[PDB]
Amino acid sequence: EVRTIKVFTTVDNINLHTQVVDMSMTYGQQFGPTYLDGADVTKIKPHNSHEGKTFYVLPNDDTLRVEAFEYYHTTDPSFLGRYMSALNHTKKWKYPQVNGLTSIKWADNNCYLATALLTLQQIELKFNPPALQDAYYRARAGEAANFCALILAYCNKTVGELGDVRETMSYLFQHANLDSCKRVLNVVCKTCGQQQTTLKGVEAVMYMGTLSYEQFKKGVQIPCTCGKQATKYLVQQESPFVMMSAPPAQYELKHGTFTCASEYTGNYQCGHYKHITSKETLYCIDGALLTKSSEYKGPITDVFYKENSYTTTIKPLEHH
Ligand SMILES: [Zn+2]
């Protein structure tokens, strides 16, 4: 009289927990919010075809809470639901291989995600959460739906929202092992003298204000804390890449002088990202579309450079 089937529940798709579900009640009535491959099945009853399948549930007991933290590195109770909500969409996107890199076909305003995804495959970055490590590798094999859904969930962004590549990279870098990265800056005020700062982690690899790594080495003009104009320059850099960003402006990209870059067309409220990469020549990846040219000048907002160890030769005459 009581009909049942056996399913597995999980929060990480690795640790599977056998469950016996009553076929007269919905999954929601028994588990709470329940997902089958991203699809919200909270309000449907178990079907005979569901036997043996794996369902995601929210981490609502001590065992699941530990498993979710160990896999995702966040205790945010909303995280799994936001991941599943995004995955229901990203599993329908297409992930073509374009010039040896996994891209995303245009959909749901995902151009900024495609540009970030392409960049991540070209810089040396190790993710700390197993969820991101595993999904990054699957994305490299062309199965990028989980990686894209995780990026959205870690960024607190939903499918369909417009986005910013620099912002997206900054949030992902929070989840990368960058604690060997180091940046030493000097701000030289003609009155106050020299003021040196050491940055670590995400702050050691990102700079907002110029696209040019060379210009950052030579010095950029900024207001000193006293209100006068000062000069800031890079003293020492220890990292495998650096990201230089600025609001989009016409910028010449020379083959072999950079790793990749973000082109931004349109305006600040309604823009389009494309990805420029330097290989044997210059390539532009626009979703599934590929173009090439020997030279490039256009509206750039991020440039990524290779690095290992840099020490300035600048040695100011000033004081302090
Ligand atoms: Zn000053």
Image (cartoon, helix red, strand yellow):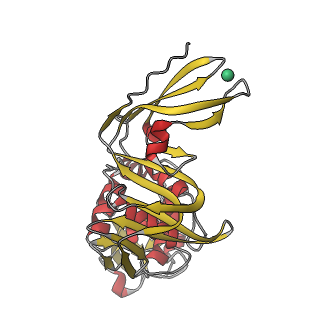
| The N terminus lies in quadrant | bottom left
Depth order, front residue of 231/184: 231
Viewed as shown, does residue 62 lie left or right of 310?
right
Q: Residue at x 57, y 58 (%)?
A: 156
Depth order, front residue of 67/277: 277
Depth order, front residue of 26/162: 162
Depth order, front residue of 24/231: 231
Viewed as shown, does residue 218 lie left or right of 16?
right
**Relative image position of residue 319 (x, y in whole percent):** 55, 13
Farthest right residue in view: 227
Q: Quadrant of residue 277?
A: bottom left
Farthest front residue in view: 317
Relative to 167, residue 291 above or below? below
Q: Residue at x 40, y 73 (%)?
A: 284
Farthest bottom residue in view: 48
Q: Residue at x 51, y 67 (%)?
A: 263
**Relative image position of residue 314 (x, y in whole percent):** 43, 27
**How many labels, in total?**
0
**Relative image position of residue 155 (x, y in whole percent):** 53, 57
| The C terminus lies in quadrant | top right
The picture quadrant for ligand 1 comes to top right
Relative to 211, residue 196 above or below? above
**Relative image position of residue 98 (x, y in whole percent):** 32, 77
Relative to 259, residue 109 above or below? below
Viewed as shown, does residue 11 lie left or right of 24?
left
Q: Is residue 39 visible to the viewer in this orientation of the structure?
A: no
Q: Is residue 270 visible to the viewer in this orientation of the structure?
A: yes
